[PDB]
Amino acid sequence: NEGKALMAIKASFSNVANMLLDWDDVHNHDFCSWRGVFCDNVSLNVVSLNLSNLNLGGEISSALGDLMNLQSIDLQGNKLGGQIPDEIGNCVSLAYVDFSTNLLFGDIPFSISKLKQLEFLNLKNNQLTGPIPATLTQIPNLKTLDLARNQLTGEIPRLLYWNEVLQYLGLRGNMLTGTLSPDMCQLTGLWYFDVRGNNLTGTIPESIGNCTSFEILDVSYNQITGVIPYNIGFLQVATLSLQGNKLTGRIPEVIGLMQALAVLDLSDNELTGPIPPILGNLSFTGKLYLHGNKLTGQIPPELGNMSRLSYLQLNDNELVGKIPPELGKLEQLFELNLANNNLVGLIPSNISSCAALNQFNVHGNFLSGAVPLEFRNLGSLTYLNLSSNSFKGKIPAELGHIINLDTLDLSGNNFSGSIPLTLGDLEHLLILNLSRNHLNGTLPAEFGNLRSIQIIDVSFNFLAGVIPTELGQLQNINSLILNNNKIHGKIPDQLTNCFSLANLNISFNNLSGIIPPMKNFTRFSPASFFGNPFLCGNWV
Amino acid sequence: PGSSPPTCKPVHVPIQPEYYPEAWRCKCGNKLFM
Image (cartoon, rainbow over all chains, first blue to last red; front, top):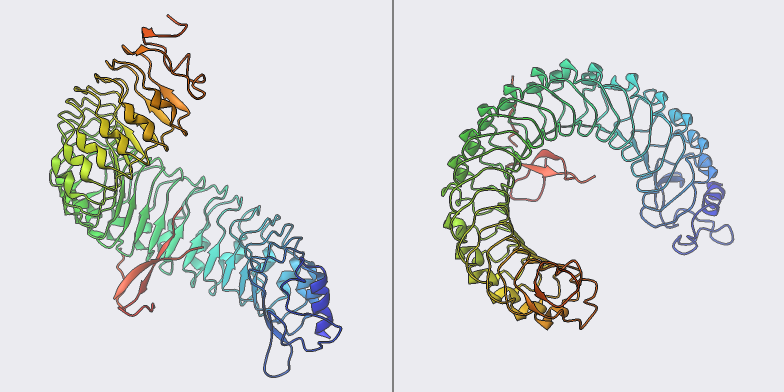
């Protein structure tokens, strides 16, 4: 007779008639062989139900209340709709509920409390509204509660924090006001505490340190204020994510002794004061993110001692001082982000010792001196941004053999000398910005070999010679900017074949001839060519 | 006052539910984890 409820369950469903392998009250009265519905060996009644990821796009019918021996329901990924019917509060045998990646709205029924055996509730990726029903600490068996990526409201129920059993608490993405209660450390079995993306206010409880059972603590992207307490230094956390809050004060030195940290993120906060050198002893941490803050001071060389660190982000701060060469000890370094600070001095020649080094970003600082050549030992270098600085000397030709370079940004500097021909051999290059510099020499032609290039900018330099004629080869180029140079000769007609080129600027030169109008080159007539005297067109 | 990693060969793993939050889990050469 549970087959009847299975039919009504099938009735208000998606056009499943497709994949539901034969549920029917016509002939087959054996509903323990049907697709996705499992019966136990003993009494032949439904125990487990796996309809996961079938795109059955219906509503959850009320007849679910009639399936009594039902223990586990997986309706995940079926694009299902409606709310969760109240009558689910019937089957007390229910244990596992996965409504993941569906489209369900409305309040979570109060009847959910009537399921004593229920230890796993996952409602992530749904449209459910309402609050977190306070009647959920009534369920004694609950270990995992995942409500992440929904729209729930109201504070976090205070009584829930008193549960020895709970293991995974995921509230990430809702709009939950209220504050972190100290009762948070009365969760003695929880190893994942995830309140990120809420409208939460308040402070960090001072009792946060007495939570040695926590492995991942993610409070990021809320309105939490206050200092980072001393107690934070007792946490056995593997990942500690404090980024994107309004925390003030300095960085507690005692987090130095927190080597269980794998990922430490303090970014986008309002923290001030220097970088604590003691952080040199967390040699097992992989990600250090400190950017977006008001941090002052120098870069302590002790960060070279974090052997297992791969991502260092210190951008958007107020740091000063030279770049220390001890980062050359970071043989596992991948990303170095030092942007929008006030650093001065040279780029150390001992920094070319971190082979695995994808992105290097020092834009927006006050660095001086020439560019070291040993950058030719960084073969895996995919990103190089040195813009808005005072760099001198020629462009080292050795920058051409870093074959996988995808973006090369040298703008805003004092670079001199002609352009290296060896810059032609970056096939995977997309964006080459040499603008706002002091470049001598003429314009080299090997720029035809940038197949994937999208954006070329050499504006505001002293380039001379004729506009190269090979520039029509680049099909992926959408922007060609050559403003304010000494380029003469005529405008090559081949500049028409740039299919993707919708953004052009060649004004302010000694350019001669006509404006070739093969294709629709009338969109870039007036403005793009303004500053050239010997150009045929109606302007001064 | 402090913390220290575990000793089962230890390693730190992403768990996929932006980046992934990493937790401590020990695997030897064998692809297991505990």
